[PDB]
Amino acid sequence: LPEAGWVGESATEPEGVIPTSKVTWANRTLVAEEVAVIIPVPEAVIDDATVAILTEVAEQGGQAIGKKLDQAVIFGIDKPASWVSPALVPAAVAAGQAIAHVSGVANEFDLVGASNKVAEKVALAGWAPDTLLSSLALRYQVANVRDADGNLAFRDGSFLGFNTHFNRNGAWAPTSAVGVIADSSRVKIGVRQDITVKFLDQATLGTGENQINLAERDMVALRLKARFAYVLGVSATSVGANQTPVGVVTPDVTA
Amino acid sequence: LPEAGWVGESATEPEGVIPTSKVTWANRTLVAEEVAVIIPVPEAVIDDATVAILTEVAEQGGQAIGKKLDQAVIFGIDKPASWVSPALVPAAVAAGQAIAHVSGVANEFDLVGASNKVAEKVALAGWAPDTLLSSLALRYQVANVRDADGNLAFRDGSFLGFNTHFNRNGAWAPTSAVGVIADSSRVKIGVRQDITVKFLDQATLGTGENQINLAERDMVALRLKARFAYVLGVSATSVGANQTPVGVVTPDVTA
Amino acid sequence: LGTGENQINLAERDMVALRLKARFAYVLGVSATSVGANQTPVGVVTPDVTA
Image (cartoon, rainbow over all chains, first blue to last red; front, side, top):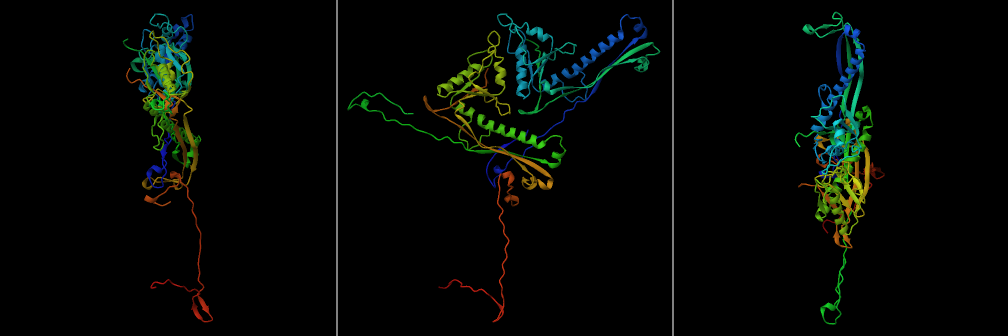
């Protein structure tokens, strides 16, 4: 951001001179990286099975690619070294936008309260928090938070103002986050190639002592691949330079 | 204000004498002061850029001027020395119209309690508190203050009877104030000249080794300037002399 | 306007100026007259420096 100043009147004294200042811009990249698997199987097993095994292998491999994308983007697990944007949980922690959930009785740090405290930090960065990522644990746990008399504290939907998405492909790392809160206008996923299947019947897998020549072993395989990119729109806002658009509710380790 | 008395009629005892008394006035001033910036850029960069750089520079410069005005008026940060009126937060503190927030469980000094106590101080001064200034933190924090059982106090209806204005240009100093409550009839902003833009293309910026001759370097610049004034109507109300029309909720630095 | 310690850059000091200019010449027609060559057409009363 540029910077104005209060200025005097003088033809001679330095306080009479209007300050110079600059706006500046920076560059964020989507870089497409490849995620893939090969699943080999005997051609005799494909012939004897009563169900289309290769259709199940294609669907299971598609789900395994979907898991590996969420792991990279949300938690930074196995993230490609060319993705210069920090993953959502590491970004929130490094920015100081992390709050620890306190379990037990209803509390200003219960699942509703700790999420409100995180959205407050994202709002004070000048971003608009609008999206909550979580495991299903949060959905069942909010439904059973008790006040000090033991009645339900949150008998009705209390995450209003968040679009809520539940991770169900097992990518969630519950030791890293209870939930992730973001301004979803500042997170983009680049889809360079959606998931594709190729049937292999002559290909060679591995090398040396691990070499599998598919044709002479009477085998086939599926190759599953996709290309994805991620960018986090960390930028200046009206509040200041270098503002992170994401925060995290961490678990808490005792009490 | 003048002061009356009771007279016990007598030609000779001092209780028979009507007391003489006095009314007085004072002068409050609007003094216009100048805030400005110059933003120089190469004319080739204006031509090669894919966006109107001079338009974004004008709007970013306008925002940066707006931040200096809010900093001066609310908090006294870089307040021009010719403005004799105290800034809204220093005024409220010096008048003894500051209430410390007490964070944690809902209590008579929580955010709603402290705002009520401040407004009743302004009302007992004989002013009509009608305006609340704060950052977005206040809106998130009243939405999560808990009763002693841990339930949400204040589901709805907080801060009715105030026009509420939220500061988003980064001028707010959360270490100085949680919120400012004022009678907005007694605060005036003088606009001697609104945000005014000149395009410079022959001008010289700086002197000696710092000198940028714009024309022989193929550069241009925007000059943005405005003149603003501020006055606070500290004056007698029906309750007494020299009453301040402003109170402040100060942050909790002790719980 | 000016240079170094005297330099006023009008734009960054929020100033303006007027430049006023004119161009003039003068000639005295010292010439011959019927009396002779090189005759000056002007005389002066100079002030009393002695009383």
